[PDB]
Image (cartoon, coloured by chain):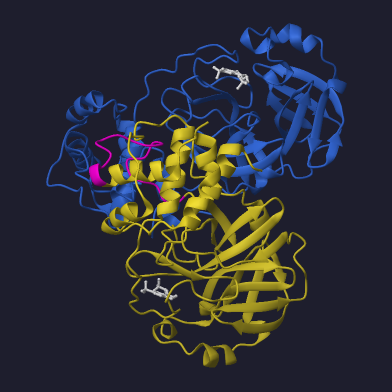
Chain colours: A blue, B yellow
Amino acid sequence: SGFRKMAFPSGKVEGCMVQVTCGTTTLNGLWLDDVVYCPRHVICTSEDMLNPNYEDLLIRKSNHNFLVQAGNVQLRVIGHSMQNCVLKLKVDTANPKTPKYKFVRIQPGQTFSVLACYNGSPSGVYQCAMRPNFTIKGSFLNGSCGSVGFNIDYDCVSFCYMHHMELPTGVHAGTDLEGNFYGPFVDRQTAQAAGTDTTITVNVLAWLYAAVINGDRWFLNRFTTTLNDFNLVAMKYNYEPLTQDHVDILGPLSAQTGIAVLDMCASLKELLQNGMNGRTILGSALLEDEFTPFDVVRQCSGVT
Amino acid sequence: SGFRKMAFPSGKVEGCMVQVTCGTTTLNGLWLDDVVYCPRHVICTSEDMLNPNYEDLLIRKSNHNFLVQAGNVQLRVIGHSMQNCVLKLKVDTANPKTPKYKFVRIQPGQTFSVLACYNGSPSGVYQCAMRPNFTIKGSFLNGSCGSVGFNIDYDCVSFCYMHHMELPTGVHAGTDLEGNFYGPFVDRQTAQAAGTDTTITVNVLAWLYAAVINGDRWFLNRFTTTLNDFNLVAMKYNYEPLTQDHVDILGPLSAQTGIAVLDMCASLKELLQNGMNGRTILGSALLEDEFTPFDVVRQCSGVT
Ligand SMILES: CS(=O)(=O)NCCN1CCCc2ccc(S(N)(=O)=O)cc21
Ligand SMILES: CS(=O)(=O)NCCN1CCCc2ccc(S(N)(=O)=O)cc21
């Protein structure tokens, strides 16, 4: 028992991290097969980042200007192309440590592990959620760009995120591995508004199920509710509206605990309206929304 | 910016995880050089765990009874010995993925990453603290025994923990890599009292410094205190007494922020006495104690 914010083991991704230097800028790259993927802003200087013309900037760069270093060995760049906001550097060597992988674009509310890197070197791993407003609340300092987010299913690594920037609000923005930003963000040093963020309701309910499984049951009450009545309360507290699809995904947890989804919603409604009264749930004094129903099932059953 | 409960990249430890089977019991082992380390309770059956005589139980076991499997290849066991609560299985092959490593016995209050494993396979990684009462609040299900805790300094993995058991209270107990339990715990299926746990005061102060560095400054006040006055309050709220050694370790954070340690203590005193008034610090509604002053410095400076 016990419930932790667990990240995936990062080994398969560590073997893909490289350092990419272009001019005076150095960030992280992802080496899969014979391609190195990195944020296209590696070609910008401090003057450029304010209003960069990436097409014009990339034209002044040749294969020999992209310095890709894997650990201590230098990779030979034989091709360069820009796909949306990522650069794809074709190298002459396939990464011998390339795991089985997919590029996937996650949905808001889904979770993933981030391997924070600097100079192509991994420093730490943590689990986070793609916020409903398409930002992530990570831990990224200068040089962390090109650090990636992923999920692991047995031997397959699904890369879902590449870090590009920190907004003036301190939240983080990035792209999928095809270089498409999550959200309305652009790779430009300009003030950018992240949408109104909401709490991922289905994840909070999944976490309440995880709490019941582990013994924290004080919040369970003698009440029930309807999807419509629950959503009136969810709207008032800036929670994502619960849909029947969310109820269906909570099915296995509802089955395991014997607590109907709408009964769990009534507990959540009471917690939203009354607060925690100084108590904690799974060692937390707030309602946790960065565990999906799949995370709860995996953790609560020991999926390796 | 941003502050996350970051674990070390687990790759160097993933390459050391093996499955160890003895009779009908299977748990995790740690393969370093030509030795596989695992909990000695791998030799117990369900009857044995209540009052095991490990010396007598191990005598009925020969090298051929310990089944050690690394991924998909079987290891040949050529020696077996018990050192405190761990078994050391000498294998005929040195692990080609053995990183530079040390066995270290951590102090209470220190942090480490845990690579939770099942059947020798890594499922997730998380950061935790060795509680002042020598327990850890982990996430461990049946089969997780033999999962290890570690710290990483550049290329050196310092193994500090091996999981052995869950107490009836749901907290976790284990040993250092020499098989010595942290705390008063024994590897016996009997009710065992963990001491009164206290909050790691120096870690809370380190985390308040991390908050100031990231912009959460609402808790800073116009007050100061003394070590003696602070400790009167720390005792009332079951916080570890702050020593000059703790003040000295907070030195770099105090220097970076320009907030004297005793001034930070006055803020903490006010938070202990008034609560958070519904506010959060670094996205947390309680005082976090699982970040050491070294963790804060490393994270806030990007140490890889
Ligand atoms: C952190 S730095 O010295 O400004 N380097 C350039 C970062 N830089 C490139 C990537 C795009 C981007 C977007 C926003 C912003 S910010 N935080 O609003 O100034 C900076 C930015
Ligand atoms: C989890 S199990 O089916 O009881 N397997 C034996 C575990 N088992 C071996 C390791 C030592 C130990 C210590 C305490 C306890 S408990 N939680 O108090 O029963 C069980 C225990």
- Of B91 and A224, the residue lying toward us: B91
Q: Residue at x 15, y 40 (%)?
A: A224
Q: Which secondary structure type mostly characterizes the magenta part of the structure?
A: loop
Assess whether residue B88 is covered by the magenta stretch.
no
Q: Does B245 appear above or below A37?
A: below
Residue A22 spot, x, y in % from top left: 78, 22
Q: Does A156 appear above or below A137?
A: below
Assess whether residue B286 is covered by the magenta stretch.
yes
Residue lying farthest to the left in this orientation: A222
Residue B149 visible to an observer of this rendering: yes
In which of the image's four quarters is ligand 1 placed? top right
Residue A6 spot, x, y in % from top left: 48, 48
Q: How many marks?
A: 0
Q: Residue at x 48, y 29 (%)?
A: A136
Q: Quadrant of residue A62?
A: top right
Residue B303 spot, x, y in % from top left: 64, 42
Q: Does B167 appear above or below B271?
A: below
- Of A2 and A296, the residue lying toward us: A2
Q: Residue at x 29, y 25 (%)?
A: A238
Residue extent of the magenta highlight: B273-290
Q: Quadrant of residue A240?
A: top left
Q: Is residue B235 left or right of residue B289?
A: left
Q: Residue at x 20, y 28 (%)?
A: A233
Residue A175 spot, x, y in % from top left: 58, 24
Q: Quadrant of residue B185?
A: bottom left
Residue A151 visible to an observer of this rendering: no
Q: In the rendered image, which quarter contains the C terminus of chain B?
A: top right
